[PDB]
Amino acid sequence: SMNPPPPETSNPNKPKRQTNQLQYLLRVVLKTLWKHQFAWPFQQPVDAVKLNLPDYYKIIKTPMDMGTIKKRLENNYYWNAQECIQDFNTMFTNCYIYNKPGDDIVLMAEALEKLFLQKINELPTEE
């Protein structure tokens, strides 16, 4: 069992805009989460081959990771901040679905999610 292609991160035909909120998501939220001690499993698409998880992509049909989110932000892929917030939420939820309560990786995701929620609380209001 193979890795899928990664999620789409750029699309020339898709309209682009920069908002205060999208800027904060890249410069504050993504940055802070990337540097967390527990970020490393979430910095790239789940590598089902290297990690020997042949059923991962049979179960998880909306994979998401911070590598992809970074690319989406820097490529102006999102029209709305809520789309990016949804990607972060998806990343955490995938981990909770695939793994069991109390697994190390779940505790890691929970700590990242708490930090995420803290930073999102300070999202600026639209310009």
Image: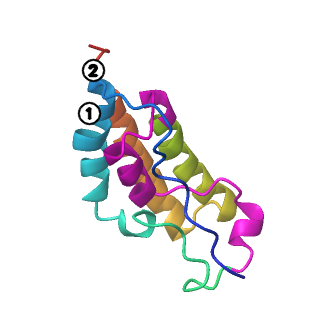
| 51 shown above or below 110 | below
Q: Quadrant of residue 95?
A: bottom right
Q: Position of residue 84 (x, y in %)?
A: 46, 38
At numbered mark 1, what does the secondary structure look like: helix, strand or loop? helix
Mark earlier in primary sequence (1, 2): 1
Q: Amino acid at mark 2?
A: Pro
Q: Which numbered tag is attached to residue 34?
A: none
How many numbered tags mark residues here?
A: 2
Q: Is residue 114 left or right of residue 50?
A: left
Picture quarter with the N terminus: bottom right
Q: Amino acid at mark 1?
A: Tyr
Q: Residue at x 33, y 35 (%)?
A: 118
Q: Are marks 1 and 2 in contact (CB under 8 Å)?
A: yes
Mark 1 and mark 2: span between their CA atoms?
8 Å
Instruction: Please name the residue that numbered disc 1 is placed on.
Output: 24
Q: Is residue 30 left or right of residue 84?
A: left
Q: Residue at x 49, y 36 (%)?
A: 14
Residue 73 within the magenta-colored segment of the rendering: yes
Q: Position of residue 106 (x, y in %)?
A: 53, 61
Residue interval drawn in magenta: 54-83
Q: Residue at x 53, y 52 (%)?
A: 91
Instruction: Please name the residue that numbered disc 2 is placed on.
Output: 124
| 98 shown above or below 81 | below
